[PDB]
Every structure is written in C-alpha cells, then in structure tokens.
Length: 264
Image (cartoon, rainbow, N blue to C red):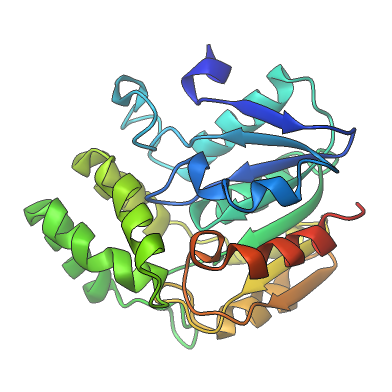
C-alpha cells in the first residue's frame, strides 16, 4: 500500500539510485525542473512525504507522525519495498533531517547525502544560531492557526527569497494544497527536532548546498554541519538567494547535483 499511498515514482535508468525527498510546503513536483539532469545517468526515486497536499489526508496519523523517526520509517519502508539496498539521498529541509536520521539507522543503505535548505536545529540555543527564537516561531504558529491563507501568502515570497514570481506562485500552490492543521503539526515536529547530538554518528559522505541567504537557515549552519558531521562533508556554495533553489534556481542547482552524484 505504501508505494501507492506516498505516490512513489521511479524514473530514469541505470544501477545508480538517487532518492529525491522534498521539504515542507511542496511535494515531489518541486524536483521537476532538476529531474531531467539526473534521469539519463540515474534511477531516480521520488515520493511525497505523508504531509504533502498530494497525499490523501486520510493517511495522516497525528499520533504516529509526532516525530521525524516516523517519516524515516516511511523512507526505509519504501526503499525496502523497492528492493533497493544502496542509494544516494537528496533531502530538502525536513527531508535533510530525515536523511541524516536514516543514514544513522542504516549506514550501508545511504552511499551519499545531499542536503538542501538544511539544518540540524532551527531554534536558537546558547551561542548556537538556528535562525529562530522560541517566541519567533510561536508567533508563526499563532498566525498559521489564526489564518492559514494569510500566513501562507506572506511566507511564500520569504521562502523563495529571490524575486522570482513564478517560483513564489508555484510554492504557494502546494503550500495552499496542505490542510492547515497538518501544516502546523509538521512544522511543530520540525521545530522540536534537534539532531546536533547525533551528527557525529553519520558516516556517509555529504554535500551541503548553501545559498547566499535563507530565511530559515543562517549562513553559519553549513559550516556547522561540516564541522560536526562524522563523514566526509563538502559545502557547495550556490550563488542565488532563497530556501528553495530547486524552484528558483534549478539550473544552478542541477549542475551541483550532477557533480555530487557523478560517483558514490
């Protein structure tokens, strides 16, 4: 059931497998523009997180998906159902956290991680800059609960960051496709997640994709990830602004993805 439930699609050709895992407010269609740069050389696995608007809301279990380990379970179950013992994994935002956790759970399964819009912790801590004070994100959660449409309209251009109207429109499309209570819930789950303690346990090589400015990811986070991840970690600097380079700068991003996924 799982493969149909999370809209799993496998495209491309080859024995080298790459998983593309999207972030909050999008579904797998967010990968559509970078996808042609990968499918000649790779077998590409796409799926929707259970919280995506493109997934039947009937399947969203608030109790089960109260932590990211439940999302990791879905990812591993998909790869097991597809009989894929080794892959590269590209994760955006919450999916970068899912990827880190998954690579610790199953080290031999993930040959390489590519992390986009990525952070081990979005809340500030003493001297650790995550990007948000507790009070800041609580204000966001208040706004999301009070009027989701109004909040979403305001957030979309901030997330896209660069002045790219088409990307703002497209991100807004899938952001509005989410049921507001599910949206709030997944955001809360992300903001109570703290992977700093386990970064040292990762052994997979890792590419961290950094843009010039990300409303949710301070510039210092990439070097922090490089410093504390336990595998070989390279920061790739993308010369463009925003949290969603696969939507707003797919050309810049695809060439980095090509390099990162050429061999693993």
